[PDB]
Length: 273
Length: 284
Ligand SMILES: [Mg+2]
Ligand SMILES: [Mg+2]
Ligand SMILES: [Mg+2]
Ligand SMILES: [Mg+2]
Ligand SMILES: [Mg+2]
Image 1 (cartoon, rainbow over the protein chains, first blue to last red):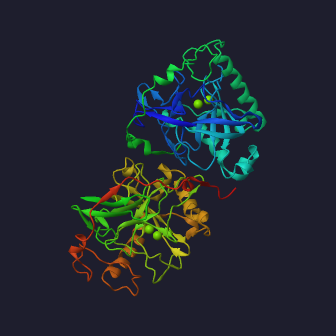
Image 2 (image 1 turned 30 degrees about the vertical axis):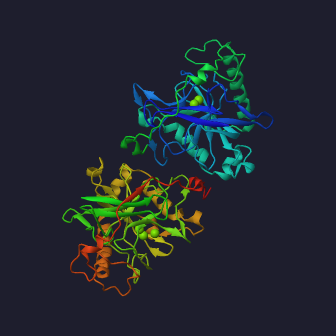
Image 3 (image 1 turned 180 degrees about the vertical axis):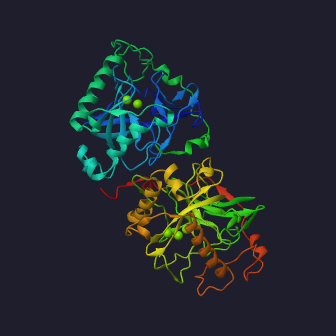
């Protein structure tokens, strides 16, 4: 059973979320199997950012057991701004564990947009099916975005491939295109671009990419990658890896006893861009 | 100074929010002056629903001193559903006090009776408001919604404390600084009850946002209807509670109605059913 352990108050620099298995912290990058069911291509997704929130929470590749923490820019907490007509992130946003875009690769686990009705929680491990994939170019890096749905979603049986997203969620792909193009403009960064004229490639294509990034991660965790520089490969479930260390689980502090900190009112603002 | 008195937990049937002056409840419908500054057309807006929320909170017409309570549908808490690409309400949503959309006459602009409540207000500024807030706003224009076949004007307004307020003087300025907002507003009020099984709404003037002058004229009309209502001279006041603590010349004035309100009993927000998360895709 997977749960979460929160350190600190939400919306502060001290905030961290670890994934626990049966009460013990494990690596959110390395210890959560990519497949919940390999034969049927059901994946475990680690959720970082709930739909309609702003705080840019991510699995941290540099910290032991890779807890989810809020991204920072020169000491300041990073929040994506509201870009009309969107409110924060427009997907449940996260990543597939045991994947790594070998750097061209963006040096992170492959990103996942989960499109189901229910709002997810930070550190949630949910099971999803892949429907398709888009290739965003962000600052000279290939930044793949897998489109997926929670297998528990009421609509999941009716969704198998990318064309079904058009049928059941008309306009979401357009919005996704737009969002990823403009979402850094309020930060003073340029508009992003997509490969393939912004087309979402189908499930078969998505599976090939996901598989590649899993194989890269297998080389990484085995200690055989060219440059694992700045990535903590500590794990507690893979006994034959060079960086296995069960003691890392017990070194994690206990759950914090703290309410969400307030978010600066500036983050409310709607930008028309 | 206006403050709030909350009874119970948000998102429950017991939840109530009274507006207080000097730590004592007053009627949110009748006792808050329409104008903060009559000469400069600065209005007091009562906020019911914060931007990007769902709970359909409103001034309760039939309850003494008209606290804000969550509306219900056949006994169950009513939440407006998320209609793609929108999340809940896309404005800070509320009303002008001391107004009434008269339900007893056909309004000439829409050829429809009024919806029997205060004139509604869409406040478009950057900061998310809170329920029971009284803020000061300037009117910028107005749209003629027919909501389930009833006259249901929506005033477009901005908080005078918004950084952009000095630059927003008339409806054309909304399109300049908030491009797409008025079109989205038209869409939102057309479609928002489709997930409830209701028909699409419509607008008079093919959804045109009329200007500030037009808005002021309609706000006056609804204020005048309210003056008749509160004097006890409406042909049909619809069981509205007219109790007030500030209008001595009215037959329902009662300073001591305030004392009878229970003390605050604020509890943490109750959880909302996960179904309210759902994003409805209406067309395409
Ligand atoms: Mg990522
Ligand atoms: Mg990426
Ligand atoms: Mg109203
Ligand atoms: Mg209405
Ligand atoms: Mg109304």
